[PDB]
Image (tube, rainbow over all chains, first blue to last red):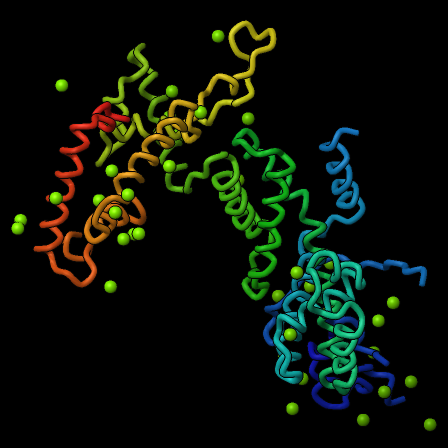
Length: 58
Length: 345
Ligand SMILES: [Mg+2]
Ligand SMILES: [Mg+2]
Ligand SMILES: [Mg+2]
Ligand SMILES: [Mg+2]
Ligand SMILES: [Mg+2]
Ligand SMILES: [Mg+2]
Ligand SMILES: [Mg+2]
Ligand SMILES: [Mg+2]
Ligand SMILES: [Mg+2]
Ligand SMILES: [Mg+2]
Ligand SMILES: [Mg+2]
Ligand SMILES: [Mg+2]
Ligand SMILES: [Mg+2]
Ligand SMILES: [Mg+2]
Ligand SMILES: [Mg+2]
Ligand SMILES: [Mg+2]
Ligand SMILES: [Mg+2]
Ligand SMILES: [Mg+2]
Ligand SMILES: [Mg+2]
Ligand SMILES: [Mg+2]
Ligand SMILES: [Mg+2]
Ligand SMILES: [Mg+2]
Ligand SMILES: [Mg+2]
Ligand SMILES: [Mg+2]
Ligand SMILES: [Mg+2]
Ligand SMILES: [Mg+2]
Ligand SMILES: [Mg+2]
Ligand SMILES: [Mg+2]
Ligand SMILES: [Mg+2]
Ligand SMILES: [Mg+2]
Ligand SMILES: [Mg+2]
Ligand SMILES: [Mg+2]
Ligand SMILES: [Mg+2]
Ligand SMILES: [Mg+2]
Ligand SMILES: [Mg+2]
Ligand SMILES: [Mg+2]
Ligand SMILES: [Mg+2]
């Protein structure tokens, strides 16, 4: 979902450098930059709301 | 036990366990339904199979086994082998198209899910179109058919949510139903509204006269082309029928249908009529010329009611000639031996 939002990982291989400052000394994004269930051409196709943790017994 | 409560509880319980969140769940499902469409179509494109076929096979795999295909739609899709063949090509679709298959099913499911969740919406709606002449369950059911209709056309791209959308698509389904089934003798929607306007108008007219409007007022107040003959006619159609089986007179044990007489059936008098009439008409028909007598006997008594087109090859002059001369010798000798005079009719 968020992959395309921050173009860094879906556009080129930059999800590793997305980990900000300690990389100089599977998904791993920035410290905390996005807060919506959207599509980011321009923050247009969105849906900012709740987040379920539905346990499927399977 | 009693039927309204059980269904009410039936869907209310499922909504109670799964209402759809305002935005999220309706968005989610919506998105899946559409992708299903785009999927099925693209499936049609790569399989050459009609989107109708792709649609029913994903339905069977998600909604029901051979059981649901065999009883509902009689038998053209082989219960097992047929649909299966279709699922096999769907599997063969590599990584790229297989994706559409997997999506189509998931989309089909979501659909049903959205439909389930928005059933309270129907009943809440259908609740007010109650006293129109349809059973509450019948009303909810048509309205239900309406919500399914909405599901087919909602474009999630256009931000508005399914609530307001279903409202319209349901109200239309209901009103139609009300106009198509409510009466024994069907009445088009226009006549219906026509009747409502007539009623409403009679209402505002009752308002001050103290005189149930003569069909004069109703015409006036109604509008452009309303006249007495029109109103007397509409309200005549407005009266629903009466129960052929109704308690009559001292309701003790009276049933309305034993009293209506019968018309096609020849009461004895008529059977005797056709006996002598046919025997005597048959006697005259024999001792004669079969040239213009049978022509007018058959043209008049055998098929339909054409002097020229009445006689075979011989023109009009021999027709009128034998018609009028044989018809009069026949009448004047029948005047002698008076058998026909006493008008059998
Ligand atoms: Mg980081
Ligand atoms: Mg790193
Ligand atoms: Mg560096
Ligand atoms: Mg470090
Ligand atoms: Mg080192
Ligand atoms: Mg953030
Ligand atoms: Mg998201
Ligand atoms: Mg925004
Ligand atoms: Mg969303
Ligand atoms: Mg939130
Ligand atoms: Mg597509
Ligand atoms: Mg191709
Ligand atoms: Mg058949
Ligand atoms: Mg065939
Ligand atoms: Mg089978
Ligand atoms: Mg089986
Ligand atoms: Mg593709
Ligand atoms: Mg009422
Ligand atoms: Mg309303
Ligand atoms: Mg009326
Ligand atoms: Mg009104
Ligand atoms: Mg009346
Ligand atoms: Mg009586
Ligand atoms: Mg009779
Ligand atoms: Mg006879
Ligand atoms: Mg004779
Ligand atoms: Mg003969
Ligand atoms: Mg003869
Ligand atoms: Mg004879
Ligand atoms: Mg004749
Ligand atoms: Mg004839
Ligand atoms: Mg004819
Ligand atoms: Mg001929
Ligand atoms: Mg003559
Ligand atoms: Mg002559
Ligand atoms: Mg004659
Ligand atoms: Mg006389």
